[PDB]
Image 1 (tube, chains in turn blue, cyan):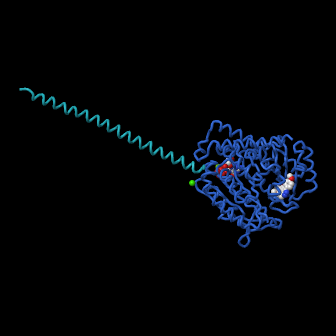
Image 2 (image 1 turned 90 degrees about the vertical axis):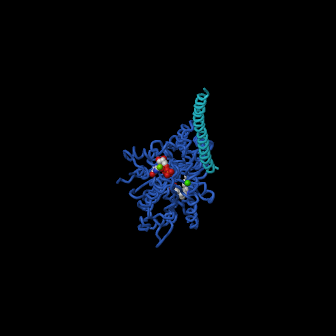
Image 3 (image 1 turned 45 degrees about the vertical axis):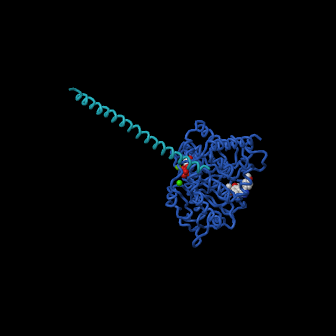
Length: 424
Length: 61
Ligand SMILES: Nc1nc2c(ncn2[C@@H]2O[C@H](COP(=O)(O)OP(=O)(O)O)[C@@H](O)[C@H]2O)c(=O)[nH]1
Ligand SMILES: COc1ccc(-c2[nH]nc3c2-c2cc(OC)c(OC)c(OC)c2CC3)cc1
Ligand SMILES: [Ca+2]
Ligand SMILES: [Mg+2]
């Protein structure tokens, strides 16, 4: 019956995790108390994938809230749908991880991780058939980045044949907490390459630009950025939450998206970008969602090639028109799909749209231009690490320079692995 | 290995601090009293002199 266990970790993790659950609890008819008050019953067919059944059969998310400080988490639970979350599923330390990967992965996080795996175990033991885990987190902080990849190291150990799937927010100098972010993120990516099956790369650069250039928000807030993420995340997961000709689970998704096991970082895109009264026509949905301006990862798809693509349209619309338009975008732009993976673009449609939009289209691209993101983070990293700058924050927690060059190395390789398939 | 290294280096830092402190207070108490030792012994060759002058003054008759 194919559940996912959702884990949100850190400040960014739990803020984005929080909106995602209100966004889709609205989509499933669940109120802030956990009680279902929807019209359809398609709202309840795949409900079990994200929600456990409850009291007078209310619905609690299958979510685990993780942090090394309580601040964000108190904020979540005193926020809107903060009541729906199982209070036992609030696992938190007190010291924080100081924007420090090592504190999350080796010291502070190490102390807390066992308590989290107790909650993952009780959430997952109550699963007739669990299919995988999805983790939300940033990679530039300490908790979501350092502890989050520790958690994945552990979940992989206890559950080696489940899918591990993350939504990962990349640091960008444009929208930065601290200067050590490329360090934290290079170290997280070394982990993600090994221990996840699929990672959606949400770049904070791109969310800023969409907010500024497109949505016309002069100075965007983190809430404005997480508006775009909770809409993409709702989008990316509608197949798992709603029934269709597609019997969509994490493993089938990974099987068709990932040709080579390391190359599993996806460029999400969304259309329309909203912060609106004419529904977009299908020809625009598909022109927009493939436009670089609607990508969440801040890489130009025309700078690389799509290994694989997965698109979904939400609303009631011409199933033939999306077929036609989808097939048409491939031939206007066949230079940008790989000749050696036949039929590498797959398209689903859902009759139920997101709140407020009558027609929406979400895009998932395994493009070799995602390399730009890692090239970007790698330049920044080297820029500091050549002068060994800010390293004391990490050597103070047991880490050695060697661990750093290995992480620099594994990511420069991943960039080579991506360039070689751009040339084929 | 990493967390037991963070522990080991925090401890060796306390260790060396603890020792550098103790060794300097010992070198200081020594040096200070040597200077007071030296100061008083100076004053006592003055006491011993103040009598070889007074005793010399009896060595007349
Ligand atoms: N998009 C987005 N990014 C965030 C948010 N909060 C923090 N960040 C980013 O996350 C990184 C900092 O990590 P953070 O989640 O604050 O630290 P942690 O609590 O130790 O995991 C920085 O790159 C911030 O730009 C958020 O709500 N939305
Ligand atoms: C590149 O060629 C392919 C891509 C995906 C699949 C597949 N198989 N099973 C599923 C999916 C699948 C597709 C989804 O997008 C269409 C999808 O929505 C995000 C989606 O939701 C997460 C899923 C999950 C259900 C098959 C071929
Ligand atoms: Ca501690
Ligand atoms: Mg922060």
